[PDB]
Length: 190
Image 1 (spheres, rainbow, N blue to C red):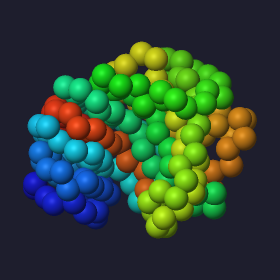
Image 2: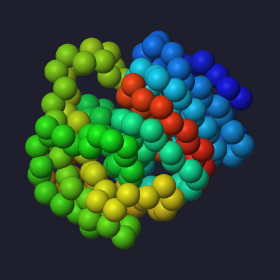
Image 3: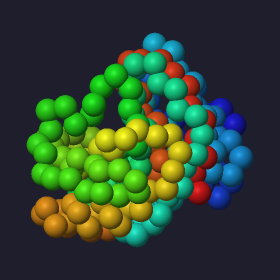
Image 4: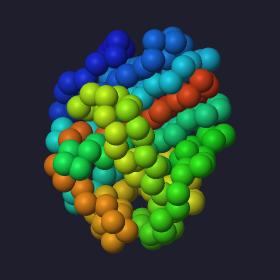
């Protein structure tokens, strides 16, 4: 069903929906691991389905339609504790590459494409544990797609070889993030 920002379990999958309060976004929990997002002249928002907690070797499958009309990303998104890390495995994006201004650490080949690895530090920003300072890890896919399989282990191993030491995995979802744009998406996670 269409819901206001929140988290929980729907049809077997953990979901998380958040928005800055700007308005213009509609999130709907669908059957199985499906969710739909329709936005128009939105603010910043993040919504998706997955697991709570996630694992370090989960192979995530996603399929559906992703039609951004501006700044938006489609990716495997999650958090880690001890160390506190916010991560993104970007599969597709709109008009803005989220790695812009980040520091490139290397590259990794996974699931039919090379990904560029980056890292950034967020100081005194909100997190799953409150206002904190943490690193943000990125894996940006060169060949964009809206359907496929993501072997998370390949990314975590690549990040580890670069100095990342993931600790306790918190939530892990396939999410659509929008940033003051418009668009629509219907993704099914499994």
